[PDB]
Length: 262
Ligand SMILES: Cc1c(Nc2ncc3cccc(C4CC4)c3n2)cnn1C1CCOCC1
Image (cartoon, rainbow, N blue to C red; front, side):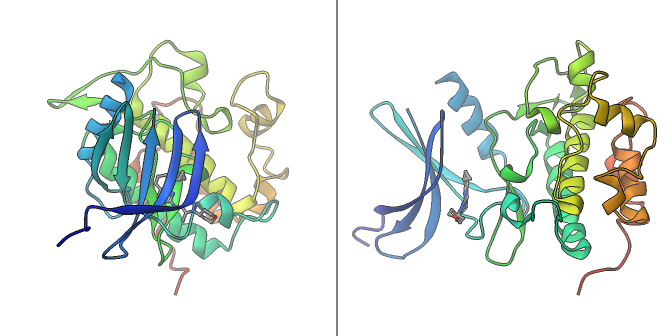
């Protein structure tokens, strides 16, 4: 069919130091996708991880064209935008909606950890929503391999977003990849349930993190979170990453399994 190769760029979806993301619409079919446009070794690594992804809760990669030294990355479009924009400041969202998002988050993180990929920047800006509000883990530009040939490799690179980062990345030289992504999913949950972030970073100098370590859940944001999800957060936001709840045990948590949503 002539012209099915052609896509019109119709809306800006995001701009950063990386380049931009454009909503693209096929000239013939009207299929809508997201095109990440960049102006070397890093994009090479990113494309390689992007090709490994095939799950309903992770953004799908359709392939890439280079024109000149400009790379175009075609991927699944999520027409409902980011989870960030469903969170009402100081309120959060309804507990059933939050639980449903957290289920989908866990499904995508399980998936990634299964294929030996860590995301390293899980936050509501990187969690996108399709036309039916299904959650898609986006942005693989910090993702890396933590398991290959069934052997684990420890991480040392400091990266992510401070209010989301686990405390071991601030205190230890090396750390396991999986407890880091689990912690950031906890902060996601807190945000959905409270419409606020609990601390600037999880350090001994941050009074809001000390308050948590001392159990002062009569303070915000914790006082806004019902006892059942707050139990779960007590098991996720544990400072020692070796004692921190794993995903298989999150799937056994009372709140996680509570029926809430129609
Ligand atoms: C359709 C839509 C999306 N999708 C959307 N879909 C897929 C994406 C894949 C990679 C990167 C991004 C963007 C950086 C976030 C993506 N983004 C994002 N934002 N949006 C609207 C923009 C205007 O405001 C309403 C929401």
